[PDB]
Image (cartoon, rainbow, N blue to C red; front, side, top):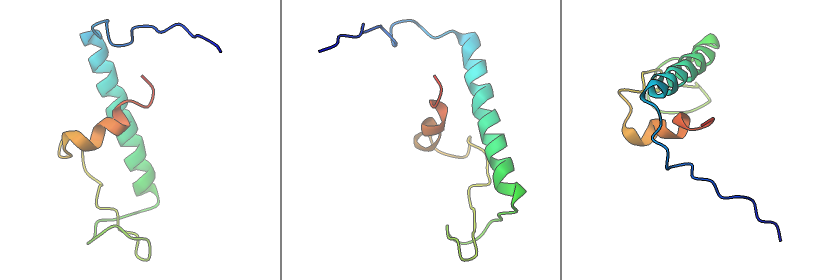
Length: 77
């Protein structure tokens, strides 16, 4: 019954200055999230669990593939 205006989210070329900002928020959310994970001293191990509570992804996002980080890249854009 309503008709909100469709706007062009994809048309404008996003600024290359902003790519520094989105990489900044990406490293910031990764660093703060890993800081949360290490603050309660989760360590490396065999597999993901809770009985010992391994955490094998205490690592950068560059080592992670393209199809792991983009879920964390667009929570706010």
